[PDB]
Image (cartoon, rainbow, N blue to C red; front, side):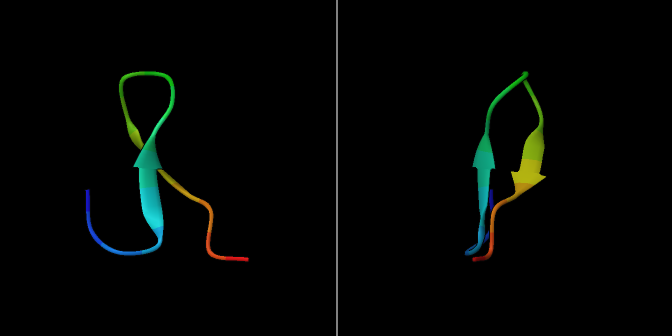
Length: 17
């Protein structure tokens, strides 16, 4: 996953906060 994104539900979710 790219910067600002992480794997949660087997998918790169946006968590840029």
